[PDB]
Image (cartoon, rainbow, N blue to C red):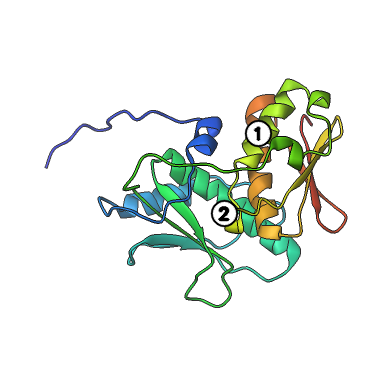
């Protein structure tokens, strides 16, 4: 056959990926080559402690990604943190995603199913930003308002949005009893802060259920 070497595609930045990421259960089948497996494998992923062993199944409809994780707090934050990086990458490639607590393997916390959306439109229900924030919204400089807004758009199991967020000047801290959801939200804060400050944020565990991002290290 014949074809252009590359047709151009709009590169969506991190803000657009977060804003265009929606949970989709109803998909098409139009395409899912090994090329998209290749694309995922080449994705540079940030990790806190250890990089997980991500697996991609495209011999099932829907297609889904997953990895084995231990049922311990830090490893599940890792799963959420790395997993949402992949979700956002897939979003930017134009794929619908949904975090599924399904798994045919009994040591996998969630799968991430993906594919082309049947539908374009969606709805986004989130509690008010002030319900998440320990600070008065007015105590936040404009960069931080943006990071918090992008963090709140993160998905969470059953949309429970289990985050408490605190800005201290140097750091943005997210606490949650739900380690996977914590990791997911932390990925949004990390990726947007990286874009905003044009530096690599440092992620540090604080106490039992909090991770802080040193924003402009």
**135 lies left or right of 107:** right
Q: Determine the residue positioned at 71% across, 28% down.
A: 145
- The picture quadrant where one finds residue 131 is top right
Return the x and y of residue 170 as percentages of the image width and height: 84, 31
N-term-proximal mark, 1 vs 2: 2
Query: Which numbered dot is residue 120?
Result: none
* Residue 55 shows up from this direction: no
* Residue 170 shows up from this direction: yes
**1 lies left or right of 156:** left
* CB-based contact (under 8 Å), mark 1 and mark 2: no
Q: Choose mark 1 or mark 2, whichever is in front.
A: 1
Return the x and y of residue 26 as percentages of the image width and height: 36, 55
Q: SS of the residue at dot 1? A: helix
Q: SS of the residue at dot 2? A: helix
Q: Determine the residue positioned at 52% across, 35% down.
A: 19
Residue carrying label 1: 149
Query: Dot 1 surroundings within 10 Å: few (below 14), some, or many (20 or more)?
Result: some
Q: Determine the residue positioned at 50% across, 48% down.
A: 87
Q: Considering depth in this image, is 49 or 23 the residue closer to the camera?
A: 23
**109 lies left or right of 134:** left
Disc 1 to disc 2, C-alpha distance: 20 Å
- The picture quadrant where one finds residue 217 is top right
Q: Considering depth in this image, is 14 or 28 the residue closer to the camera?
A: 28
Q: Determine the residue positioned at 31% across, 28% down.
A: 8
Indicate the quadrant containing the N terminus: top left, top right, bottom left or bottom right. top left
In this rendering, is residue 43 above or below 147?
below
- Looking at this rendering, what residue extends furthest in the bottom direction? 106
Query: Dot 2 surroundings within 10 Å: few (below 14), some, or many (20 or more)?
Result: many
Query: Which numbered dot is residue 83?
Result: 2
- The picture quadrant where one finds residue 80 is bottom right
Return the x and y of residue 58 as percentages of the image width and height: 35, 62
**41 lies left or right of 132:** left
């Amino acid at each position: 056959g014949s074809d252009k070497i590359h047709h151009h595609h709009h590169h969506m930045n991190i803000f657009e990926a977060i804003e265009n990421r929606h949970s989709v259960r109803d998909f098409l089948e139009r395409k899912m080559p090994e090329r998209v497996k290749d694309d995922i494998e080449n994705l540079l992923v940030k990790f806190i402690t250890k990089k997980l062993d991500w697996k991609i199944n495209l011999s099932s409809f829907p297609s889904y990604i997953y990895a084995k994780a231990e049922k311990h707090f830090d490893e599940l934050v890792e799963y959420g943190f790395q997993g949402e990086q992949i979700v956002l990458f897939l979003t930017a490639q134009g794929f619908g995603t949904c975090w599924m607590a399904r798994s045919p393997h009994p040591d996998v916390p969630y799968i991430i199913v993906f594919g082309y959306p049947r539908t374009r439109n969606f709805t986004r229900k989130r509690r008010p930003i002030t319900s998440f924030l320990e600070n008065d919204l007015e105590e936040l400089p404009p960069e931080i308002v943006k990071i918090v807004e992008m963090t709140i758009l993160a998905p969470s199991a059953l949309n429970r949005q289990p985050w408490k967020i605190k800005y201290t000047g140097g750091e943005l801290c997210i606490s949650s009893e739900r380690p996977v959801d914590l990791g997911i939200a932390l990925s949004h804060a990390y990726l947007t802060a990286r874009e905003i400050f044009k530096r690599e944020p440092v992620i540090q565990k604080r106490g039992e259920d909090t991770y802080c991002l040193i924003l402009n290290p």
